[PDB]
Image (spheres, coloured by chain):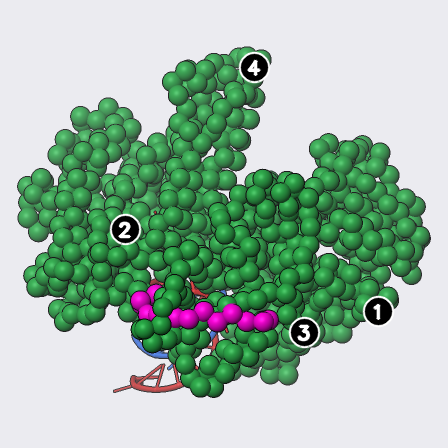
Chain colours: A green, B red, C blue
Amino acid sequence: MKEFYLTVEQIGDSIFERYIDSNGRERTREVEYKPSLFAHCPESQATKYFDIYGKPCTRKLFANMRDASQWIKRMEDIGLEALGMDDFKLAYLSDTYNYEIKYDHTKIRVANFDIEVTSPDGFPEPSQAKHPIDAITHYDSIDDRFYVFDLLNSPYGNVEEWSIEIAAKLQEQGGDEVPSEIIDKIIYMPFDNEKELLMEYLNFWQQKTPVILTGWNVESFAIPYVYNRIKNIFGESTAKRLSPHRKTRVKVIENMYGSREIITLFGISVLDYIDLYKKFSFTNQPSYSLDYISEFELNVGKLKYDGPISKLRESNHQRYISYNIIAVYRVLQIDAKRQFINLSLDMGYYAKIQIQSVFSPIKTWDAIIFNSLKEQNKVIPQGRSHPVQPYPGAFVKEPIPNRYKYVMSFDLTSLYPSIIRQVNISPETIAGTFKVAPLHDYINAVAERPSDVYSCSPNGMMYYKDRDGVVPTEITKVFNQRKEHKGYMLAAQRNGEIIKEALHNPNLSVDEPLDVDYRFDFSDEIKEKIKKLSAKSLNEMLFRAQRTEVAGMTAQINRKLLINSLYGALGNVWFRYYDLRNATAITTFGQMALQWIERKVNEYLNEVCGTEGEAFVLYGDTDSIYVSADKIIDKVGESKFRDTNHWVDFLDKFARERMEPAIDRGFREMCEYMNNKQHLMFMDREAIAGPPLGSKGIGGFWTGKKRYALNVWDMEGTRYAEPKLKIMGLETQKSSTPKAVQKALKECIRRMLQEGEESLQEYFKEFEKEFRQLNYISIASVSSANNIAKYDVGGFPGPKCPFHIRGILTYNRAIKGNIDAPQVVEGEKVYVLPLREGNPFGDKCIAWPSGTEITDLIKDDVLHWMDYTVLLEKTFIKPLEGFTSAAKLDYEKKASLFDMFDF
DNA sequence: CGTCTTATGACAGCCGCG
DNA sequence: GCGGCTGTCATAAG
Ligand SMILES: Nc1ncnc2c1ncn2[C@H]1C[C@H](O)[C@@H](COP(=O)(O)OP(=O)(O)OP(=O)(O)O)O1
Ligand SMILES: [Mg+2]
């Protein structure tokens, strides 16, 4: 098989690479790399290398990288361009790996660990690292074993060995419920002393050296902590054993309050799972404690223990060890579901970068573009510095705030990348400019055709159609990968809906979940095998369909991000090809394209419909249009449709067979009008929304820009067995909104759109009646702990100081000197509750770390002094009032004037 | 070392207001 | 002692 890299580092004049040879064995190299850079030269200077604009360059080979850096600064001291790849690590991979990398993941040692550390005086700081590590669980993907390092003896207790037999037992038999799947994969190692455990851990680290280090929060806790603890006991030299190349870096970043350390292990790609989640998950969570995320991702209970963690090792060492194990395992199950490491490797090897550079899309693209550029023997520009500058973005329509009964929506397939292609927008494909008319004339088609030689954008730019661009090129490859995985995702989602109808009446049977690829549309035979199955068999099938869909999701949405991020890279001063003429060519074209097609969509329907000058497009954002479908439904009445599904099928058939080709006609005309390389503007039918047949439900409603809800029956060819609410922007969708309140506002919106005004008031009346009974956490608001320092007037609120910030200050006074209480960390989320007048906390509100409960020290005061009236109005009724008004509804009851007829 | 603009709402403080 | 406005902040939609 082909050879592929594991890690790579630059150290001085030596490149340190770990890799896999033709055999699948893992080797290392120390390479004394001889990089090449480039400089322009006169025309008559024969050469194979040219810059991207067409200009001759001579290659300058160098003895070593220091000398190549020495040259880059001198070229600037003189002030001439130093073209080429300034980052020599990427150049070396590009040299060593002159092909498309296919990689054997089973040969890649992904390690996954967590440590435990008892502390009676509050959170154990890794900076200091002043407490014993009393447990570590290190899972190794190659061995497929969890290595448990256990400390029987410590200043904080002498404990007996952990019993696997006990750990296996269920928590109702008095055990730990450590999963079946992992009981035969634990290798357990008790230790008398710390020094011993550590040394063994280090030796173990040497023979099973992690290529990808991951885990929950390891980057800010685990890694730093083991490093410093080992460093303080055995000296810094021993600590460096953690790096296979024996080189490390300490990035101390003293927050305005206390210390904080970041350790770089050369030779290892640390991918902390917390960061991979934030980037790739497309969620904004109330809290990021593993405990919370496990719940959310896996529907799986909180690892339970009595008393505080600080004395679990002494109370119940058995539990203590088991939780450190299951903690490791959970991250493995989350990744089984989400595939973020899989993703990371894909992009990583695709771009040919260090795996941990998947976090920076600027890096990713620089390497993709360089590699692509290198094979055509072209020289890349030098990165140049730039001031930051605003530039205009997308166009959003102001919708008339109303109820909407029948709504059909349409959206462009990857707008900004398609534009990039359609127009051939790239650094080296720029043809010049042209005098631009008010954009509203290009929208209307009045303005002079800007050029009939060059491909154009309404911002005034012109592009070549002859030659093809680096960016269009590279953006197209990844787009197709996106497209493929989107295909599988959407199929899985349909297969999901087919299984959902099957369990409306499952065949009384003892059967077998079918052996099938959930990525593809269930064929007839298998659909007819489907309904003959049992609930047990069918649920397993659903579960699996769902796991496929989610996996397709990840692959799809993250590749979508990467390309959209190429666009965003164009508007970013740090990007080698940073360029605002291109960035605005994209967005301005986006604006024209969205309004242009509004006009056409509005024109065609007024035609086919009968009237003239009726606004059918009620709304649109960047690349979407939401068309009102009332008058089209009105062209057959309420009668002719048997059931709900009959008018859905209709609209779908109408969109597909009448509207779409009209759209297509419109967009290819615009393509001509703009003289673009290729027509690539596609609006796929997205949503079909309305009320269920002969019900008093409102279908949809807009409140303003970015704020609407709809009742959807079909989303992009998927015919849900249950109508699903599509809610955008409203507080139900915001992680700041209290949990129970998200659920309530949602049941409301579901009530307005499906049932009607009647149902709303009924449920509204119930909710406020029961409100005071809800769990304080479930009804707390969430915010981020930012800039506490800045607003701290020596203990009290400063000028301008925000609500949640104010809440945090009151907390910190109410926990003065108490070091057992959880402090609040900068940047992390807090729960927020308002306080009643006269409370003993001083202020009108309080805040505490989210994902956790408030410490007992204040727990019972906050619960007494809690302010429900305020909470209900600010968090539930104000929001509901917003929705209510727009929809023309009341959520309560008007002044009868017919009350005179009571009883 | 470093994706982007557009837009909403909860709040704070400012200002006018017999 | 408020409703209208502006700016800061947190957080959505694309
Ligand atoms: N995270 C982002 N960064 C930069 N630009 C974005 C981002 N999200 C969206 N955009 C811009 C460019 C998109 O093409 C345009 C419309 O976005 P959107 O419709 O969500 O997806 P898309 O049109 O790129 O693909 P698709 O509609 O197929 O999911 O808005
Ligand atoms: Mg789109």
Disc on the earlier residue, 4 or 3? 3
Instruction: Give the Cα distance between marks 2 and 4.
Output: 45 Å
Q: Which mark is residue A360?
A: none
Q: Label 3 amino acid?
A: Val
Q: State the residue at coordinates (83%, 53%).
A: A203
Rendered location of residue A700, percent (x, y): 30, 45
Q: CA distance from mark 1 to mark 2?
A: 61 Å
- Determine the CA span between mark 4 and mark 3: 60 Å
Q: Which residue is mark 4?
A: A511
Q: Position of residue A411 (x, y in %)?
A: 28, 47
Chain under numbered label 3 = A
Using the rendered image, report if marks 4 and 3 lie on a common chain: yes
- The answer to whether A111 appears left or right of A570 in the picture is right
The answer to whether residue A342 is seen in the rendering is yes
Badge 2: how crowded within 10 Å, few (<14), some, or many (20+)? many
Q: Tell me the element at label 1.
A: loop
Count neighbours of disc 3 (C-alpha within 10 A) and say few if under 14, some if 14 to 19, many if 20 or more: few
Mark closer to the chain start, 2 or 3: 3
- Location of mark 3 (residue): A252
Q: Which amino acid does the dot numbered 2 rest on? A: Ser
Question: What residue is shown with label 1?
Answer: A235
CB of residue at label 2: within 8 Å of ligand 1?
yes
